[PDB]
Length: 323
Image 1 (tube, rainbow, N blue to C red):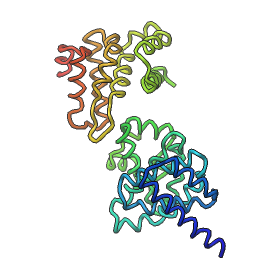
Image 2: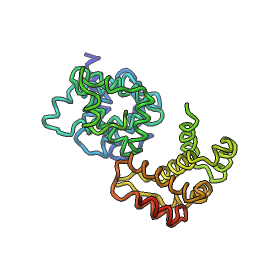
Image 3: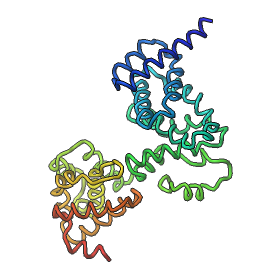
Image 4: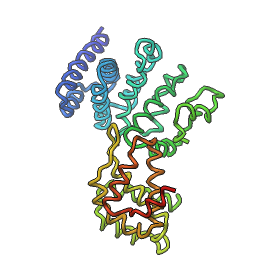
């Protein structure tokens, strides 16, 4: 039938488009080609094919495919609904593939995660929709877990947990009736998933740094936004230390410290870390930070070195911290 060939032809073109994209990596060309299909109600096929063809290709291919879908979504060519339709077609068969493809869930997470980027789908909505096919499987956790893993890798479990929480997400929503959340979370190692001016502070400092604000801009902001008591508080010290050190994390594998960032912020930190007491309080904060990053190998020491080198934390504070 016409409709039959239509689906055939579309898959054919999705293949051509997808193949060229993975080969040349020209995002803009791929996006336009999809647009030229002018078949919004059949893009589930494109999605399905993209997933199928890259599932066992490579991590990089899955990444590129995920990014393209996010782009298509963002450009308004691929509807959320069509995206889900295409995925469901494969998520439905996931459990079965697990037999021959052990890390299938991981591969799926690698394909979906890019969708969480700005302009994409909100975590709460994504997690809730994406898991319907797994409502039957009773395997919702298998996927979300791999997704949370990827996110952690790129931003830290702490921030991930906050994202999860802000979405009002609950494991109850994804676990079999009666399963002990406390246990599951403890066993799968996701305890991290479990306004106050002090918390607002963290959010604002984070934003300031995220937007590449100069030290003066931050100095001014603090002066313009906190009271005298707040300005000399340990709370500011801890929040500042945390935001600054966080902004210096390079999320590669393994994680590293961008000493150039620290050097650039040294003066900002010295200003508030004006005594041994405050320096110590800052070290505690940094420590708790690294802890949330799951004590990666000797990353703390890397911060210590840079901090000592930049004259941000002096010897005595280090001595005292040792206790």
